[PDB]
Length: 161
Ligand SMILES: CC(=O)N1CCN(CCCc2ccccc2)CC1
Image 1 (cartoon, rainbow, N blue to C red):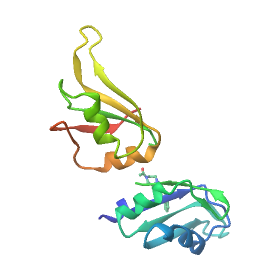
Image 2 (cartoon, protein in one colour; image 1 turned 180 degrees about the horizontal axis):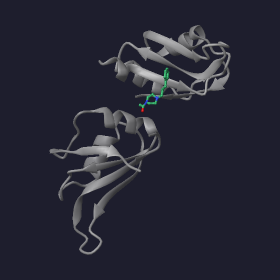
Image 3 (cartoon, rainbow, N blue to C red; image 1 turned 45 degrees about the horizontal axis):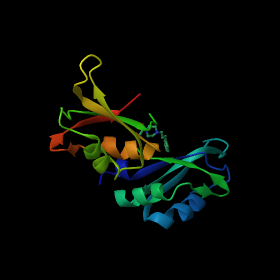
Image 4 (cartoon, rainbow, N blue to C red; image 1 turned 90 degrees about the horizontal axis):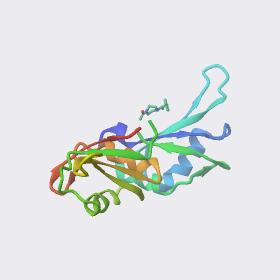
């Protein structure tokens, strides 16, 4: 997989976290090909964020599924390669129902709201929907896929608001 899709940016680090301690933590969920704490070029003081690179996307998934991560005593904020919990799903036409969207998207994350859009005047389905999840990583996984097939339709999916 492209390296960009195997990275996790890690915000909110303890300033005492090092390359070595960040690595020892995140190696619990996969092989790390890279692990860096960002520091000031003059003082060497941590900037409070870094990144790790796993060998595979499944390892990224395992790390994200193991949140919350407390690294060196502080809960950190990992994100993949803006942070929203809602998607627009277009191209679903008039025959797509809630259960089609739920059965597919529930495998990306926990769904809180499905809104199938209807015409304000006639009530007819407009052919698009919004899905809201309990967490942003679902959306991040969704929007990096080239394709989404739901109810036989190839759908357009994008972050919403
Ligand atoms: C997906 C996306 O929009 N982005 C991912 C990267 N984000 C910032 C990471 C900055 C960084 C971290 C670690 C080493 C160097 C630099 C913001 C942009």
